[PDB]
Image: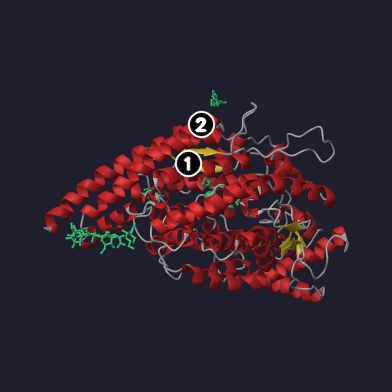
Amino acid sequence: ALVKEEIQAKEYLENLNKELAKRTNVETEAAWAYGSNITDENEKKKNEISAELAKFMKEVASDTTKFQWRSYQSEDLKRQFKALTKLGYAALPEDDYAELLDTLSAMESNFAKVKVCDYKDSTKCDLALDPEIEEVISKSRDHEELAYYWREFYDKAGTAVRSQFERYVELNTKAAKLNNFTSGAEAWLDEYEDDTFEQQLEDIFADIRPLYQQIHGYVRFRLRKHYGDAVVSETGPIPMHLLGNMWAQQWSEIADIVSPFPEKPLVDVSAEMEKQGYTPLKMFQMGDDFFTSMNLTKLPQDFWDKSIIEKPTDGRDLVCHASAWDFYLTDDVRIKQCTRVTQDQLFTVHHELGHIQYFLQYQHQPFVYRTGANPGFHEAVGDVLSLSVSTPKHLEKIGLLKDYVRDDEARINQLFLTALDKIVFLPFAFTMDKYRWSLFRGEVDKANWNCAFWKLRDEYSGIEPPVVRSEKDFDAPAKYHISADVEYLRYLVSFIIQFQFYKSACIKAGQYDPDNVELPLDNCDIYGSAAAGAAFHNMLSMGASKPWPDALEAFNGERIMSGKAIAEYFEPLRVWLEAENIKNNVHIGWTTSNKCVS
Ligand SMILES: *[C@@H]1O[C@H](CO)[C@@H](O[C@@H]2O[C@H](CO)[C@@H](O[C@@H]3O[C@H](CO[C@H]4O[C@H](CO)[C@@H](O)[C@H](O)[C@@H]4O)[C@@H](O)[C@H](O[C@H]4O[C@H](CO[C@@H]5O[C@H](CO)[C@@H](O)[C@H](O)[C@@H]5O)[C@@H](O)[C@H](O)[C@@H]4O)[C@@H]3O)[C@H](O)[C@H]2NC(C)=O)[C@H](O)[C@H]1NC(C)=O
Ligand SMILES: C[C@H](N[C@H](CCc1ccccc1)C(=O)O)C(=O)N1[C@H](C(=O)O)C[C@@H]2CCC[C@@H]21
Ligand SMILES: *[C@@H]1O[C@H](CO)[C@@H](O)[C@H](O)[C@H]1NC(C)=O
Ligand SMILES: *[C@@H]1O[C@H](CO)[C@@H](O)[C@H](O)[C@H]1NC(C)=O
Ligand SMILES: [Zn+2]
């Protein structure tokens, strides 16, 4: 009967979890070796271990049907068994799984090996995205130079893998249906355990959208004064190569030319970092210090011994795109980052260390629970710290910001600077998955795949390519996450919920009072707050043991994803910016782009 079986099932799960952790450790090591050192030998090794683990998962999924798990009394045991039914790609027949793995590594390695020629010297053709091309995109204000690097990169990282991407969509769809989801869109959405999740995001996005339109309008106005009306039109989408980022996902690199008050200070601490002799090691030690100051977990010795925190100086190929790794043992956690000494990189260091902290907080959990409450939670942790490290308050403490007077106009500059990252990112993040959902669901014919991409980038972000594109190009995979098959909705969710976490953490730290002008949300520093740390410990140690609303409740008593906190943060900017656009008769909104020929 069921009473004896449930007792046996508990013993089965305890053993199986340990076995899965150990088998996944082996797969992860292989994936790490390939990511740090791209070779045909390492690819073969990585993909063969994965096929072996997939085969074992099939046996596991099959074995769950032998247990009457849906009949059990324990919610915890049922939740664990349910986790074990979720095969994903491992549901594919042996040969199809092997083909998908070959397709995925072909795309990620193509991206990682992209090299372009120097604009000024066609002899020098060893310029990688990280750091060479990104340096030019972020620093150059020569629109024809920017356009050149845009075209070269997108042609190599995007168009070159069209056929591979098509096969990936086919196999992703096949895998989803084998798991009885309609498509890979629904498979991705299952991670959020909420049948109204899409609508919830539409609703939140609609509330923030008008603020984005105002920022867009003002930035376009300021770019016209810089580049002139031949380069930037008043009424059209912004030419994306002028926004200081290869994908126009963040605009903070052009802050010096679009800032509300150019005679008042704009925080940019890169020069001081360099002056004070900062290194990648110091940046990571500072990040570690922040976490420990909050009474959270110190980085283990394995992290320092095994991480790769600087780009290797031999001729080898690797994935430089920053990442954090869990090896599912004890204290074996690693970062791989091609760290540069800049302000934005300091934020990225904290982002990645947020992942590491999460890994450490839930490593005592059974294997199936050793992941985020939802994917957005994992992305939010580090960004919460980054919000406080970016404050004038904190940057002055660590001696990176000198002779700073925090008047109303400096405050507006800082809010605007933050918005150029945080608000600008929202429509970007939404479109990355909206696009892939539409392909996964079979809503766009293959003949229209590229213009379907640029249509969304137009509709939501109001940006366009610097040159005319067509269905002869394929631009989506020029973004890492698209080439590497990493779901993007996590970042949209993160950018919303991180303000929920930040606001609550700041109240707990005594750093925010809505009725005290001395304690504004935009100058909150949670450094050294054990009270904020405690809330994180309560939430992060849970892992995926409970549905995400219970994890949020453990942090601050709330159970709902809400746009209230992000709106509250930027409210002073909104009021000012609305008035400023009216003062300057700034055109808001945009005409449909002519940059993608059907
Ligand atoms: C995605 O959805 C799929 C459905 O679209 C689903 O596929 C179905 O899975 C079922 C297994 O859960 C499977 O059901 C079995 O069918 C066998 C015969 O099917 C054949 O004939 C049918 C023609 O009429 C065709 O439609 C099929 O294609 C096949 O040719 C049965 O022999 C089998 O039975 C046995 O198992 C049941 C289940 O027992 C359960 O557990 C305990 C036993 O330990 C019971 O006490 C309990 O009550 C419960 O019933 C026993 O009752 C029985 O005695 C037999 O031992 C079973 O019904 C079905 O064939 C399959 N396909 C289709 C088209 O329906 C996928 O599994 C889903 N995938 C995922 C990942 O979720
Ligand atoms: C740098 C970071 N990269 C990693 C990608 C994660 C990953 C890496 C490899 C395989 C699967 C997932 C991350 O930590 O999420 C990243 O791409 N982004 C996103 C991005 O740059 O697109 C925005 C997020 C806010 C700050 C940086 C974060
Ligand atoms: C990269 O891998 C090759 C074999 O594929 C190995 O011989 C070499 O040591 C690795 N290089 C580095 C720098 O680790
Ligand atoms: C630090 O954390 C421990 C347990 O994680 C807790 O017992 C202790 O009270 C914390 N320190 C402070 C000052 O709250
Ligand atoms: Zn992340």
Tell me the SS state at disc 1.
strand
Amino acid at pointer 1: Trp
Name the front one of labels 1 and 2.
2
> Which residue is under mark 1?
325
* Colour basis: secondary structure
What residue do we see at 61% from left, 64% from top? 518
Location of residue 52 with respect to 140 vertically, above or below: above
Q: Nearer the viewer, residue 143 or 386?
A: 143
Using a 10 Å C-alpha cutoff, classify the residue at mark 2 as few (fewer than 14 neighbours), some (14 to 19) or many (20 or more).
some
- Mark 2 lies on a secondary structure that is helix
Label total for image: 2
Q: Position of residue 303 (x, y in %)?
A: 48, 35
Image quarter (top left, top right, bottom left or bottom right) of the C terminus? bottom right
Which of 386/179 is in front? 179
Which of the four quarters of the rendered structure image does ligand 3 lie in? top right
Percent x, y for residue 78? Answer: 27, 58
Q: Position of residue 230 (x, y in %)?
A: 88, 62
If you read the primary sequence from the N terminus, does the residue marked by circle 1 or circle 2 appear first?
Answer: 2
Q: Which residue is mark 2?
A: 42
Name the kind of residue labelled 2 in the image: Asn
Label 1 CB sits under 8 Å from any ligand 2 atom: no
The quadrant of the image that shows the N terminus is: bottom left
State left or right for residue 564 relative to residue 460. left
The residues tagged by marks 1 and 2 sit, at their Cα atoms, a distance apart of: 18 Å
